[PDB]
Amino acid sequence: PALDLIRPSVTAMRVIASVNADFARELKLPPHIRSLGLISADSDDVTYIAADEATKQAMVEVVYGRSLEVLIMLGGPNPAEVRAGLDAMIAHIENGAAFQWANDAQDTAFLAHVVSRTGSYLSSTAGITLGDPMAYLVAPPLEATYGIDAALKSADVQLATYVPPPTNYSAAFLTGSQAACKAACNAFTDAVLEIARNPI
Amino acid sequence: PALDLIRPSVTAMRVIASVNADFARELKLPPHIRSLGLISADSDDVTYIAADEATKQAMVEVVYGRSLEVLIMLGGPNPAEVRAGLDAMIAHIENGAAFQWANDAQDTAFLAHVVSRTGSYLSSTAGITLGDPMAYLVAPPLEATYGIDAALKSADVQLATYVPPPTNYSAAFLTGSQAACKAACNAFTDAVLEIARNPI
Amino acid sequence: PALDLIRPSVTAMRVIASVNADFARELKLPPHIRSLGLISADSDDVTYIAADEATKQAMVEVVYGRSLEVLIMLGGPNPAEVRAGLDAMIAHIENGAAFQWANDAQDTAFLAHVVSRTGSYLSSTAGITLGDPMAYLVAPPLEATYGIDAALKSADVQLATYVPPPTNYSAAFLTGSQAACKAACNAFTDAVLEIARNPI
Ligand SMILES: [Zn+2]
Ligand SMILES: [Zn+2]
Ligand SMILES: [Zn+2]
Ligand SMILES: [Zn+2]
Ligand SMILES: [Zn+2]
Ligand SMILES: [Zn+2]
Figure 1 (tube, rainbow over the protein chains, first blue to last red):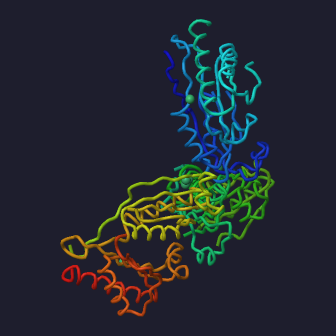
Figure 2: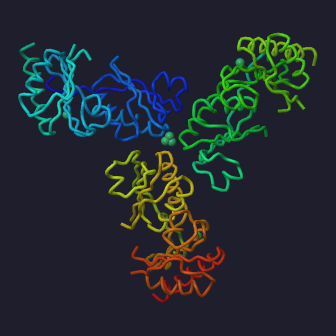
Figure 3: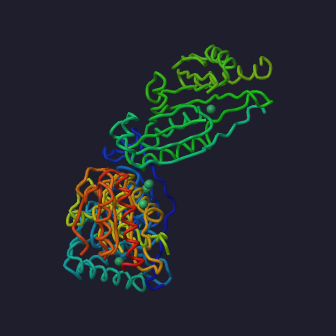
């Protein structure tokens, strides 16, 4: 209704304890990576954030990950490090960051979370130092653009990465400090809400 | 009765997460191998084929394996790679290659499977390139010899390894292509069946 | 009553598959150690002996461990080696070495076990060769001192480590042979029992 979460979910899972010679290659795989985790899920950005958050709890890395709703192949040395990694992705997936509705009619959904310590997945899919804070904002395009601008007019932050909307949602990440990351966040959600009630 | 499978089974299992200094030695163990998998089973050849098939799914290798009905000690770096290995052996053991009866009286049992991509266990217990196809034929001695010959007179194949029968069954492996590996296979089973009905 | 065991127990557990950069450091952690096991328990000495006994079953080592009743952080390369390690600590904890009562009134408790092959935890918290036998004697202070002396007057053994009592119990370790380790052990328990009935 208001800002009620949207529990995302895990739809499939499977570990490949020892990726083929020929697969690791075509796949373009560091030598050190012979184990593999396949995770899929519904929300992309909420998985993106998991992939990230499991790059900190197991020595793993996101070999891959795009919107289908998703797929994230987590790479690691032995399986036991990609397990803990997957088992974490789930955990940050089944109960962590979540979209939210922006109207009551439940038909215009947004996403304002703060990543306080980027693991290696977004530090990198966004010109950043590993760990720097971040504001991951996802909303419908138009609802999106207007909200960033606001975002920005709200805190000393910068666009930390930005090809625009053309997810069928605009997403964007803003760094700066981390409180400022938060206000910006707040202000993103208000923007997007004034429009979902009355702009749109 | 006819060619009804003979489900083999797993009788025991145990991982040794960290083999003794002194055991690894007497055992003649590569340094890289400190974990160990003990598997036992009934059918030998069907385990042999598992040992093989788990050498492809976990970075493991068959440190050992002979007919007792069996024992296969799988070697690996950490345990988590010998687990996935054992868990696979089982899987290819509880539901994969299987002996079959050759008479109806259920008392003369054979084994004709095709290993399309040898892992490192048989490529090696048979002058071969790693992965080359293969025809693993097991049958009572006499039923055995007559059937190979046939085997051979059936497809362009070669004996890829062969000390003869003297398992209480003759076994033998034939390489060549892989279709030819199959006909040879077919022709092995017919041979062995004409005798189990009427030669024997 | 007499010498009835005192089952110790495991109160908490948790694996940290990938210890922080900054934690491993402050913690003073070999590079090779990125996985971590936290175990806690009631009896200290009985955990001490586990920590030890799991240093032999998984490639792990006791990064830490003191009396609180306890905490033992087990260090290892991947998690799969610290798991097997923890799972062993438990096993030698839930069913192995155990305190015992020394009176019937159940209020003066002792501990006489023989560690026949020290792993790396005590070989080292006691000038010893890795594996040398050992006699780990824990008893109330006074009950303690009198009993060692006896200990010693009983077998050719040596104090293998000794800051005295000031556990709220004196503990001490005696090496020598391993039978002699045992008599010494026996004689420690009698001593401590003559006093728990009548000295004390
Ligand atoms: Zn594991
Ligand atoms: Zn948030
Ligand atoms: Zn595992
Ligand atoms: Zn077959
Ligand atoms: Zn494991
Ligand atoms: Zn004892």
